[PDB]
Amino acid sequence: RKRRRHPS
Amino acid sequence: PLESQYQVGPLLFGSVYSGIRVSDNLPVAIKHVEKDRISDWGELPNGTRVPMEVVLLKKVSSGFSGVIRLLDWFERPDSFVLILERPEPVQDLFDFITERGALQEELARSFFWQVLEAVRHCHNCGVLHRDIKDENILIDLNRGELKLIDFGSGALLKDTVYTDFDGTRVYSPPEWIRYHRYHGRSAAVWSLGILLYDMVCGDIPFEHDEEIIGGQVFFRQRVSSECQHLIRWCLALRPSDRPTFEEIQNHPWMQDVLLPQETAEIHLH
Ligand SMILES: Nc1ccc(/C=C\c2ccc(C(=O)O)cc2)cc1
């Protein structure tokens, strides 16, 4: 399961 | 003189450079913010119009090590430059959870408690961060102290309704998803619930709008009942059903926290 950053 | 006071190093999108204060070889972060890209502005006591981020950083700058300290700032024709504290050695909490996976509850407790104190500090100073997440939390690996960073989405703390938001959608509460409104404290508690799940399960629980408003929390990792309950409480669909900061820090799962130095010796060295 791919974990990722999330821009703001 | 900006380039005459700091030795500028390499990048850390977003434009933050590693730097050293030539005065005392102090590690700093040098952050550039384009004027054309600035959401809210504020006025300093001088009346000099500055980005709201500068205003918020100054209001929280009073000495408590849980929040990143703004050391200086400069104005340029098309941008502002922020000189910020840089711990060294450091790693942000997002990379830390990526490398290590789900955290032991003892370590998640210490981190989450430190985030809670830091957010209390912001609110006491009249500042609402609005973008609490693992990416905006730095770990001083030798002191075991957490730092909250990037106030670029923040706002002055108020008790009335907010109808604007520029933080991270997957950490925003269902009332923002559904109705474009929220109150500051209860929306922060929701993001703290997302953060806590993120620490003990190794990733955030919700990626999609329907999941956020669904009010269902599935645990992918073995997580104690007391911790699951605190998480579910923070993630109450109704904002008024969420715990206060005091209720969170009195929760049974939050008792007997490690000191920062114990945390560094046991989990970081
Ligand atoms: N991954 C990583 C590494 C080093 C730093 C340094 C410090 C810093 C950077 C940005 C900010 C801010 O946006 O308020 C503050 C401090 C930050 C993140």
Image: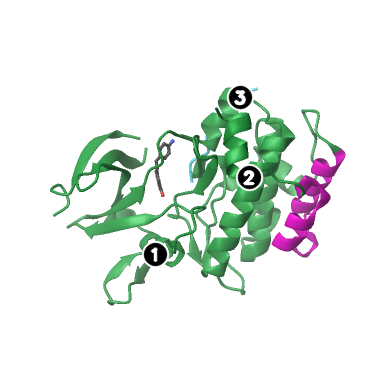
Chain colours: A cyan, B green
**Distance (Cα) linking label 3 and label 1:** 34 Å
Q: Amino acid at mark 2?
A: Leu
Q: Which residue is mark 3?
A: B100
* Label at residue B259: 2
| Magenta residues, start to end | B225-254
Q: Residue at x 21, y 55 (%)?
A: B78
> Three-letter amino acid code at disc 3?
Arg
Does residue B221 lie above or below B128 as drawn?
above
Marks 2 and 3, how far apart in space? 21 Å
Residue at image location 44% in from the left, 64% down from the top: B62
Residue placed most toward the observer, B198 or B251: B251
Secondary structure predominantly adopted by residues drawn in magenta? helix
Q: Secondary structure at mark 3?
A: helix
State which chain disc 2 sits on: B
- Is B205 displayed left or right of B123 in the figure? right
Q: Secondary structure at mark 1?
A: helix
- Residue type, mark 1 in image: Lys
Q: Nearer the viewer, mark 2 or mark 3?
A: 2
Task: Count residues near mark 3 (Cα–Cα under 10 Å), then give few for <14, some for 14-19, many for 20+.
Answer: few
Return the residue nearer the eye: B80 or B215. B80
Measured along the vertical axis of the image, is residue B149 above or below residue B217? below
Q: Position of residue B200 (x, y in %)?
A: 71, 34
Magenta span includes B182 = no
Task: Identify whether B228 is placed above or below B40.
Answer: above
Please give the name of the residue rendered at 55% of the width and 62% of the height, measured from the top-left corner. Answer: B121
Ligand 1 neighbours mark 2 (CB distance < 8 Å): no
Label 2: which secondary element: loop
Q: Give the image location of residue B102, x and y in percent.
A: 68, 28
Task: Identify residue for label 1.
Answer: B58
Ligand 1 picture quarter: top left
